[PDB]
Every structure is written in structure tokens, then in C-alpha cells.
Image: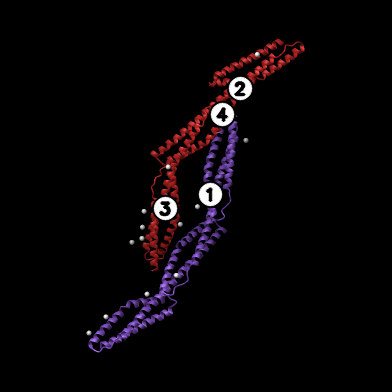
Chain colours: A red, B purple
Amino acid sequence: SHMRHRLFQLNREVDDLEQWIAEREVVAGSHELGQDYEHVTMLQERFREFARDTGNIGQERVDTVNHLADELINSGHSDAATIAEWKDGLNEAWADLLELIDTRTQILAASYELHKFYHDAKEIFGRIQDKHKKLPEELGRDQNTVETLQRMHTTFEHDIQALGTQVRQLQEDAARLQAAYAGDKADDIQKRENEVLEAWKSLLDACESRRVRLVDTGDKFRFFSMVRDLMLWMEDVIRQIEAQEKPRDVSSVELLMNNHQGIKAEIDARNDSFTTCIELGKSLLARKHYASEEIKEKLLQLTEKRKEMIDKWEDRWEWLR
Amino acid sequence: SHMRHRLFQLNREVDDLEQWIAEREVVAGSHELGQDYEHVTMLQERFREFARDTGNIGQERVDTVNHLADELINSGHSDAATIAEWKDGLNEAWADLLELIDTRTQILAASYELHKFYHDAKEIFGRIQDKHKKLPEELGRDQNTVETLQRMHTTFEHDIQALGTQVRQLQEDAARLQAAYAGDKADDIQKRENEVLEAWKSLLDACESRRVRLVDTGDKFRFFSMVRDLMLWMEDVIRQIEAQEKPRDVSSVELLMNNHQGIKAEIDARNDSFTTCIELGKSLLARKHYASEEIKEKLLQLTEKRKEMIDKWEDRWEWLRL
Ligand SMILES: [Mg+2]
Ligand SMILES: [Mg+2]
Ligand SMILES: [Mg+2]
Ligand SMILES: [Mg+2]
Ligand SMILES: [Mg+2]
Ligand SMILES: [Mg+2]
Ligand SMILES: [Mg+2]
Ligand SMILES: [Mg+2]
Ligand SMILES: [Mg+2]
Ligand SMILES: [Mg+2]
Ligand SMILES: [Mg+2]
Ligand SMILES: [Mg+2]
Ligand SMILES: [Mg+2]
């Protein structure tokens, strides 16, 4: 009759607990669809709290009821068959709930991952386009400004590799998600990934086209500066020659021939500078440079000035003979 | 000199990332285990976040720098040999940081479970000792008060069921940790476990001793009560028989014989009550009740009074019916 009370008490506890499990099953059984990334995020985080609260509270109560029932069954209570029936029904209900919590937790993780893909694709896409937009058209005005622009571009191309990394990550996510799904869905992931890859492709193509144009414009201004330096120098040598005073005695002839021969040494020492300059110019022509017409003009001006200079040197020498 | 710019640019990114990795490694390399349960709980959560952030931020940066280094090597940069040296060492530093994060996660997890065992053992030992301090000693002085105390002891016994489940959980935790470690640490755990189990046992034995002494005490009062009810009744039946007037004519004799047979009817109606009472008394004696001497005296007073009542009823009936 103590065993009578113990039995009546256990019945109460089992009924209380199964009622509590049924309450939790309503929540765990929710089929609520996430409307967008923000909402699925909320859903997942709420249910993670719920799963943990449910497990914490329920496991202890289930263990207590199981203990009470096992004590009565093990002691050979005359209602052992009924008591075992109670215990089985409870353990089944609890196992079913935990299974359902598992299934919903999975479904919400899958959904989260899928919404996150579309989210990251929107964000990478926007970052790509925003970067594409900050990309100068101009090549620049002289040697000094072109080399600054070249260095800025080198930094820009540096400063997009981080987006590249994010693009490759998106590609891996798309791959993982496409294995999960099929039909309409795996298709839409492919399209979305493609939109981002094409935007990326276009940014790189534009960075490469700009790198190349800056090299071309740089080479142009390099060539022009080589020509200018030679032209200025040649005019100096010509003026040097023009400044020479006709000798009035043998010691003056000797001095002037020595000085003039010094000038030939100056001239000859520039041979490699002419070669470097002319080779570059001829290179640019071979590659159909946009400034080919200027470049021929400058090559012709250089060779006409060089002839002026050599003619003037030879005329002076041969009259000093 | 383009190629030089890219080299120095990479150089900076490499040294920067390595700095950043060194900073994360200081955090991952902490040897702080937590001063108590609360502390290690917090340590553990905060590094959980740290490990996630570090891995996510870190991996992208490493991968970014590898790509840039690989671009330079693949295009035959003059310093490809040196670049590959920077790259290789960065990757080693990153992989080292990742293993170190796994290591810290593991020993935080281990510290957490050890702290928690000692936190639970102290909580439970304290709860058991507190419950045991609140166990009453009084058994009651009458049937009603025993009944009340029994209700209250039932509640007490109910109150400690969840406490039992916590003790059993601690035993589970104790065996798992004892299997996990060994030497003086495992010994320390078994020591703490046995302390709780002994207090638990002490409480359970006390609750059961009380439960039983309350049943015994209540049964004694209930038996004494049953005997008293029968004694008072019997003495009144004897008084009713003794009050009867000697009949003086045939009609009176017939009326009295009827009324007398009515009295037997009333007497015989108590057969179940006597049986219940006597069986209770006998049940206490086989129990070896501590009041056995007084229970025996009462059984005898009861049966002797019933024999007296019956004898007086029968002697009256005999004299009447002749
Ligand atoms: Mg039921
Ligand atoms: Mg259901
Ligand atoms: Mg919204
Ligand atoms: Mg049945
Ligand atoms: Mg059921
Ligand atoms: Mg002139
Ligand atoms: Mg934890
Ligand atoms: Mg070396
Ligand atoms: Mg009281
Ligand atoms: Mg368990
Ligand atoms: Mg009674
Ligand atoms: Mg008659
Ligand atoms: Mg009558």
C-alpha cells in the first residue's frame, strides 16, 4: 500500500512528463519555411536555444522517471507489466522528440547554407562591380605620371586578390551545395555562381587591358625621353665645335686637334645610348604601337641630328689636318 | 622595376600576416585553465568564438597571400627562390596555429569537465547535507499527528528523487573521468565521488528508517484506537444487559427475549471489527513491535471483555428462555 502509493505517484509523473514532451513536439515539428537569409538565421538560432533547453530539462526528468519505474519493476511489483508499459511509452515519446529535434536542426542548417550562398554571391558580386567602377581610364601625361599610375595599378591588382579569394570560396560553396540538390535548385546555384564568375572575369580582363596600355604609354615616354637626352647632348657637341677658335700658331693647332679628338671620344662614348634608343623605337614600331607616327618622326629627327653632328665634326677635323 | 614593386608589396603582406599569426598564437598558446567552473566556462566560450574568427579571417588571408606568391613564382620572378621560402614558412606558421587552436580547444574542454565534476560534487554534497539537516525526528503522539507526519515524509521522499538522479549522473561522470585519467587525479575523483555517495546513502537510510518508524507508530495508535472503540461499546452492551428488568408476565418475557436477541444481533455485527482489530494486534507482534508488551495486554483485555459480554448475554438468554 506503500507500493500502492509509489505506483500512483509514478503514474502522475509519467502523465506530467508526456504532456511536457507533447508541448515540445509542437515546436520541434514546425515546418516553418525561412523567407530569406535573415529570417532563416533567426529560425536556426531560436531552435538551437530550444533544442538545448529541451534536452537540458527533459533528459533529467526522463532519467528520474526511468529510475522510479525500474525500481518498482526490479523489485517484482505485481503491476510490473503496466509499469513497463508506462516506461516504454515515455522512452518512445522522448526518443521521437529528440529525433524530430535532430531532423529540424538539419533542415534548418541546410536552409541556412543555401540562403547564405545567395547572400555571399550578392555581396561578392556587388564588391566586384564597385571595384570595377573605381578603375581609371587614363594612362597619363609624362614619364613621371605614367610610372605613378603604373604603381597605383600594381596596388589595385594587388588589392583585388582578396576578392578573388572570396570568389574561389563561393565556387567551393556552390560545389558543396550542388551535390546536395538537383533540378531547379542545383541549376539556380549554377546560374548565380556564373553571374559572379563573369563579373570577376570582366574585372580581370579590364585590369589586364589597363596594365598593358600603361606599359605601352610608359614605353612611349621612355623612348621620347631617350631621344630628347640625345638631341640635347648632340646640340651641346655641335655648339662646342662652333665655339672653337681658328688656331693662329702651331701650339694652338696642336691644342685644338687634341681638344677636337677629345670631342670624338665624347661622341663615341654615346654609341650604346644611340643603339638602346633606336632599338626601343624600332621595337615599338614592330609591335604597331599607337604612337608609331611620332616614333618614326623622332627616329628620323635623331638620325638627321646625328648626321649634322658627325658632318660638323668631320669638317672641322679635316680642315685641322 | 615593376617586378621589384610587386616583390616588396608581397614582402609587406607576408611580414604583416606573419605578425598577425604570431598575435593569434599568443592567444591560442595560453596556459590558463580557469580558476573555477565559472571561469573555465567563460574561457571556453570566448575561445570558441576566437577559434572560429581566427580560422575564417586567417584562411582567407593565407590563401590570398599564397595566390600572390604563386603568381610571382609562376611568371618566373627573379626572386622566385626567396618568395617560395616566404610562402613555405607562412604555410607552416598557419598550419602550426591551426593545430595549436585544436590543442587549446581540447585542454579547455578537459579543464571544463574536471572543474564541472568538482562543481557538481560540491553542489550535490551540499544539497544532500542540507536535506538531511531538515529531516524531522518527531513521530507523533496520536493517530492524526502520525498521519500528518506521514504526509509530510512522503513529500520529503518526493523532494529528493531529482537529487538521486543528480547523484547517479555524478557517478556516470566520475567513471568516465576516472577512465580518462589515472594516478592521483583519478584517485581524487573517486575520493570525491565516494564522499557524495556516502552522504547520499546516509540520507536514504535515514528517510527509510523514518518512513518505517512512522508506519509502526501509526499502526500502534490505530490498534489502540480500535481496542478502545470495542471496549467502550462492550461495556455499554454489558450495562444494557444488566439494566434489563425481570419480566413478570408472558408478554414481557416475549418482549425482553426479542430485545435480547436484538442485542446479540448488534453483538454479532461487530465480528468483522474484532477480526480487524485482533489481526492488527497480531500483525504488530510478529513485527516484533517495541510496544509488544502493551499490545499483548490490550489484546487480552479485549478478548476477556468480549468473553464477559458474551457470557453475560448467554446466561441471561438461558434464564429467560426457560
Ligand atoms: Mg496513464
Ligand atoms: Mg505526437
Ligand atoms: Mg527580410
Ligand atoms: Mg493491459
Ligand atoms: Mg503511451
Ligand atoms: Mg646653329
Ligand atoms: Mg559546453
Ligand atoms: Mg637562397
Ligand atoms: Mg507539523
Ligand atoms: Mg544519461
Ligand atoms: Mg480506527
Ligand atoms: Mg416464542
Ligand atoms: Mg431488535
- Please name the amino acid that badge 4 sits on: Leu
Chain letter of the residue beneath label 1 in the structure image: B
What is the x, y in percent for residue B319? 28, 88
Query: Is residue B172 depicted above or below B69 in this figure?
Result: below
Tell me the residue that label 1 is attached to.
B46
Quadrant of the rendering where the C terminus of chain A is positioned: top right
Q: CA distance from mark 1 to mark 2?
A: 62 Å
Tell me the residue that label 4 is attached to.
A149
Tell me the residue that label 2 is attached to.
A225
Disc nearer the start of the sequence (2/4): 4
Residue neighbourhood size for the residue with mark 1, other residues' Cα within 10 Å, grouped as few (<14), some (14–19), many (≥20): few
The reply to whether label 1 and label 3 mark residues of one chain is no
Q: Indicate the quadrant of ligand 1 in the picture.
A: bottom left
The reply to whether label 1 and label 2 mark residues of one chain is no
- Please name the amino acid that badge 1 sits on: Arg
Residue A81 image label: none
Residue A98 image label: 3
Residue neighbourhood size for the residue with mark 4, other residues' Cα within 10 Å, grouped as few (<14), some (14–19), many (≥20): some
Element type where label 2 sits in the image = helix
What is the x, y in percent for residue B108? 54, 51
Circles 1 and 3: CB atoms closer than 8 Å: no
Q: Toward which corner of the image does residue B80 lie, by quadrant?
A: top right
Circles 3 and 2: CB atoms closer than 8 Å: no
What is the x, y in percent for residue A91? 40, 57
Q: CA distance from mark 3 to mark 2?
A: 80 Å
Q: CA distance from mark 2 to mark 4?
A: 18 Å
Residue at 45% x, 66% y is B156
- Mark 3 CB in 8 Å range of ligand 10? no
Q: CA distance from mark 1 to mark 3?
A: 28 Å
Chain letter of the residue beneath label 3 in the structure image: A
Quadrant of the rendering where the N terminus of chain A is positioned: bottom left
